Amino acid sequence: MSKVTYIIKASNDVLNEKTATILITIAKKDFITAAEVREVHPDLGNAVVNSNIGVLIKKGLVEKSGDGLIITGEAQDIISNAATLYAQENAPELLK
């Protein structure tokens, strides 16, 4: 169900699924790249995937540290907050 919807929640209705997962993929990995974000995805979607990283970038949040992408403080609050919202409902092993 899982975390991106919570990312959307935590950010405050910026993300979709698509940007939430993409911001996540970068956010986790310090010097990912855009390439890796392309490379992972099952279900981001190559055309969207280009958009989602850039659209984070054009806001903030992610900062490209070049040559991989890595997130600002702004993301870092969102991801921590959102993952915690994941934690309540998923709860790896946490609540259940």
Image: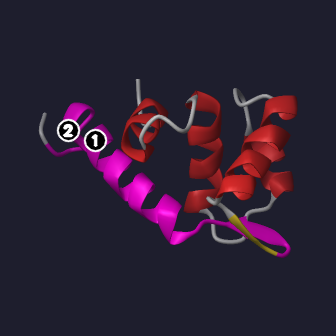
Structural distance between the alpha carbons of marks 1 and 2 = 5 Å
Figure check: 40 above or below 16: below
In the rendered view, tell whether residue 23 sits above or below residue 52. below
Categorize mark 1 by other alpha carbons within 10 Å: few (<14), some (14-19), many (20+): some
Q: Quadrant of the C terminus?
A: top left
Amino acid carrying label 2: it is Gln
Res. 60 image quadrant: bottom right
Dot 1 falls on a residue whose secondary structure is helix
Region in magenta: 66-94
Rendering coords of residue 19 (x, y %): 63, 39
Residue 69 falls left or right of residue 74? right
Residue 20, position in %: x, y?
A: 56, 40
Q: In the displayed structure, would residue 70 be above or below residue 7?
A: below
Residue 26 locus on image (x, y percent): 65, 57
Q: Was residue 76 drawn as part of the magenta stretch in this picture?
A: yes
Q: Is 23 on the left or on the right of 39, as rendered?
A: left
Q: Name the residue at the top extreme.
A: 1
Indicate yes or no whether the magenta region holds residue 46. Answer: no
SS at badge 2:
helix
Residue underneath mark 2: 88
* Image disc number at residue 85: 1
For badge 1, the amino acid type reads: Leu
Q: Residue at x 85, y 73 (%)?
A: 67
For image coordinates 23% across by 39% down, the residue present is 91
Residue name at image x 36 percent, y 46 percent: 82
